[PDB]
Image (cartoon, rainbow, N blue to C red; front, side, top):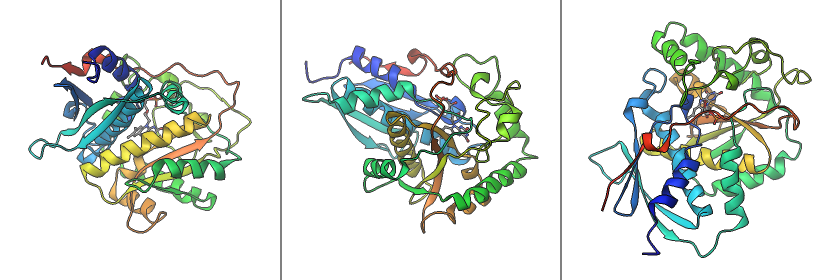
Length: 327
Ligand SMILES: Cc1cc2c(cc1C)N(C[C@H](O)[C@H](O)[C@H](O)COP(=O)(O)O)c1[nH]c(=O)[nH]c(=O)c1N2
């Protein structure tokens, strides 16, 4: 029996992995534990319909969960093997995971699982990380030979990205659905999902972060007043194409990047609205290497170490999204 992953350990790893980030904290994943395996499905009811064409970011978010689950399970002593899109007749079935014991859990495994708990999205301005170059080498080693590529944008294109962001908001001015979705998923009365007020920034703070999606403003505040402008390094993660398979890959890559950043004490913030429209995404495409499809931007930098840290954003309980089917 000792080579079969047990429910308690699986569920504990799911509880940890569910810290994964997701578009608007929608957590659009469904899991089924059955016959010793774990099936990962998109939850179509939790797709942000106008915002996220083709459910790309919902699938991406599930990819982030996929990688998180692997990380969580490794720290628990379990290796994971993944079959992606195992059922041509159900494109909502994104992956099936199977498990085998590791011989030992490394310090790396532990630190990476600690990073899952520590990571948060930080929408305040950041300082640039002075030892970026050496860190970029670590990030690239983690991403290996694909399927997700990363471009580090030069400071000389920061304004172009900012203007692509503004263009995106302009194109959404009359998209009522986008605006109602943004309101919905930022309602202050949500408790298990959505973006809480403590995770949002004030109008004044927003003036100081050029690369951002506009969200409803939090109550007035002027945090990190020493930083007149965000100086985060901007990286773009991209894939060969824009299929569901590519979306899933993108999310696994995004998870790897966010966790690597967190393990090195770096602040992160994904920015995706510039990838949600053709016009915007093509602008970002021209900033990156030939033939690559931009999937997500990440701001990477330093937060002030003694800043108070907002509380964790909420997650759904595991019994909302994990089914266990008896043998
Ligand atoms: C695919 C996807 C897309 C986005 C994000 C994430 C992911 C995975 N999130 C961040 C997101 O809102 C955040 O992860 C959740 O609110 C949960 O909060 P924590 O990340 O745990 O702090 C994000 N945040 C942001 O400031 N701008 C954005 O455009 C987006 N969009």
